[PDB]
Image (spheres, rainbow, N blue to C red):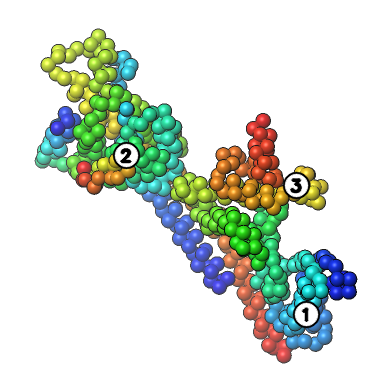
């Protein structure tokens, strides 16, 4: 990568999968090497080794290298020190959760556990940011009422809240986007939706414009237009 | 911690289970009194209906509805509220008298225009003639009931002892008595103002019956609902129990490892 | 004074005769508040 970054000076790409294996490998050798084991058993040089590696992946004035790093979280515990110190060196993360996988949403990205320093009302403008703000608030409310929902029915929630809950259930279903690489597995032809289109699609849903059609309509389908059509498909 | 936060949360769930259990039992007790009342009331109602049927009962309006102050009676409050909303599409601008808070709030959302009179302080008690009589008396004076050519009352008919279907029925105006051929099936002179008396009397008698049907449906629903709550809570006890057990084991392991690491050195 | 309000008052009076039961007393003692509402604002709750 460095040869491309530096010597060729042309923008590159980089994929790393898994950088947990990098940490893990170090922990195995560490014991044999003769180091007093650090917590969970990780190598004491965990911080330095990860640090050095992650600063050898960077965008210099010489070149810009987009990198994609894949972290096998062991037992899916983010509190584990190796995943934790990984979280520190990333510029954006989109943690994908087993729970959201169980919900059947592929992509299974947890929506309350994603961040980018590129999500800002300057970077993607106020309108995008406003759209995102409402999604976050709606989903967080939905997460908040999960206890109450389980203990007592949704009918025993406030009417105002019931609108929120219904909207959020729709948002959750809406978020699934069939993937063409996963076309085999899903059995649904993948669809890529424009950034301009995405903001529009969510904006409408947030204003409840197309909230009047089943959750199943939003389930495993692409953009807002596709949802409208899929309502017709279901309606038949 | 993990350990304590699991434990306190599990304790909460346990206490919740206990409360939902307690309510469900108490609900059964309370329900027995309610059902007894509903029989007696319905029998009384049948006598009034005997007149109206035999008479031929042929008919801004009034809408009256009943749902207690208190909630957590399942979806009694909101199934009736929804059934008001549909027939308040039907009515142009009818004045809704809401007997008890839970339906009042829901209807207030649907229109604040139509809400003119509402009650409060009914639900906690089992309906009694005293309540009905006073409610009727205020209904006549405040709402000027006769102005409405048709009145309709909404309540929850307790369809089966595990079901409730929100139900409505029409209270027959003094006009109805007048233009029904009830002269052909009964006899009054003219000295009595039998329309003005019978209207008033059946305004309350019909409402009391509706209240009794409703009260029984409320308590019955509350029993059904709190029972289903107990089941849901039990499942959560099991789910957090597994979490507790896992968490307990993990704590032992993690602490032990620290001890080993120290000892090894 | 509605006719049934007249009858109601009579019923309450009638348990005053010497022989009494709790359910009767409950039938002769209940409270509430009838609240007016506008086309909006609620004129102040007045005890039933």
- CB contact under 8 Å: marks 3 and 2: no
Residue bearing the label numbered 1: A52
- The image shows residue B241, relative to residue B161, as above or below, that is below
Q: Which chain does the residue under circle 1 lie in?
A: A
Of C6 and B245, the residue lying toward us: C6
Residue bearing the label numbered 3: A191
Q: Which chain does the residue under circle 2 lie in?
A: C
In the image, taking residue A67 as reference, residue B231 lies left or right, namely left
Q: In this orientation, does residue B212 appear?
A: no
User: Quick check: do tags 3 and 2 share a chain?
Assistant: no
Number of other residues with Cα within 10 Å of mark 2, as a class: few under 14, some 14 to 19, many 20 or more = few
What's the CA distance linking mark 2 and mark 1? 71 Å
Residue B35, given in percent of the width and then of the height, sits at: 35, 37
Of badges 2 and 1, nearer the viewer stands 2
Residue B211, given in percent of the width and then of the height, sits at: 32, 36
Number of other residues with Cα within 10 Å of mark 1, as a class: few under 14, some 14 to 19, many 20 or more = few
* Earlier sequence position, callout 3 versus callout 1: 1
Of B154 and A47, the residue lying toward us: A47
Residue bearing the label numbered 2: C39
User: Quick check: do tags 2 and 1 share a chain?
Assistant: no
In the image, taking residue B139 as reference, residue A78 lies left or right, namely right
């Amino acid at each position: 990568a460095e040869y491309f970054r530096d010597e060729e000076g042309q923008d590159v790409l980089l994929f790393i999968d898994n950088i947990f294996r990098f940490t893990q490998a170090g922990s195995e050798v560490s014991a044999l090497l003769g180091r007093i084991p650090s917590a969970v058993g990780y190598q004491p040089t965990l911080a330095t080794d990860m640090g050095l590696l992650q600063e050898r992946i960077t965008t210099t004035k010489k070149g810009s290298v987009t990198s994609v790093q894949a972290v096998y979280v062991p037992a899916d515990d983010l509190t584990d020190p190796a995943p934790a110190t990984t979280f520190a060196h990333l510029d954006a993360t989109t943690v994908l959760s087993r729970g959201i996988s169980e919900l059947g949403i592929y992509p299974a990205v947890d929506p309350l556990d994603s961040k980018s320093r590129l999500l800002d009302a300057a970077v993607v403008g106020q309108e995008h940011y406003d759209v995102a703000s409402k999604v976050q608030e709606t989903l967080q409310t939905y997460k908040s009422l999960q206890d109450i929902i389980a203990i007592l029915g949704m009918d025993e929630l406030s009417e105002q809240d019931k609108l929120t809950v219904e909207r959020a259930r729709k948002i959750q279903r809406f978020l699934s986007q069939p993937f063409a690489v996963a076309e085999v597995f899903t059995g649904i032809p993948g669809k890529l939706v424009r950034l301009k289109d995405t903001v529009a699609s969510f904006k409408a849903v947030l204003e409840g414009k197309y909230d009047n059609i089943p959750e199943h309509a939003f389930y495993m389908v692409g953009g807002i237009e596709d949802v409208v059509a899929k309502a017709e498909k279901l309606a038949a | 911690a993990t350990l304590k936060e699991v434990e306190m949360r599990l304790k909460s769930i346990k206490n919740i289970e206990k409360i939902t259990k307690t309510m469900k039992i108490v609900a059964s007790t309370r329900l027995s009194k309610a059902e007894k009342a509903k029989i007696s009331a319905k029998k009384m109602d049948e006598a009034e209906q005997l007149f109206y049927k035999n008479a031929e009962t042929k008919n801004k309006e009034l809408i009256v509805a009943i749902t207690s102050d208190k909630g957590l009676c399942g979806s009694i409050h909101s199934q009736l509220a929804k059934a008001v909303r549909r027939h308040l599409n039907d009515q142009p601008n009818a004045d809704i008298v809401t007997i008890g808070d839970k339906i009042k709030m829901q209807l207030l959302r649907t229109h604040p225009n139509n809400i003119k009179l509402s009650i409060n302080g009914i639900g906690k008690d089992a309906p009694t003639f005293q309540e009905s009589a006073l409610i009727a008396d205020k209904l006549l004076s405040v709402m000027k009931a006769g102005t409405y050519p048709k009145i309709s009352i909404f309540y929850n008919d307790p369809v089966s002892s595990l079901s409730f279907e929100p139900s409505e029925k029409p209270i027959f105006n003094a006009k109805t008595i007048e233009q029904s051929p009830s002269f052909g099936k009964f006899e009054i002179d003219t000295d009595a103002n039998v329309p003005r008396d019978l209207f008033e009397y059946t305004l309350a008698n019909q409402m009391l019956t509706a209240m009794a049907q409703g009260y029984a449906a409320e308590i019955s629903a509350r029993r059904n609902a709190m029972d289903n709550a107990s089941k849901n809570a039990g499942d959560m006890i099991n789910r957090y129990s597994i979490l507790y057990n896992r968490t307990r084991q993990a704590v032992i392991t993690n602490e032990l490892v620290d001890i080993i690491t120290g000892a090894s050195s | 004074i509605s006719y049934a309000a007249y009858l109601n008052v009579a019923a309450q009076a009638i348990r005053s005769t010497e022989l009494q039961t709790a359910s009767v007393l409950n039938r002769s003692q209940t409270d509430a508040f009838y609240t007016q509402y506008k086309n909006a604002s609620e004129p102040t709750p007045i005890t039933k």
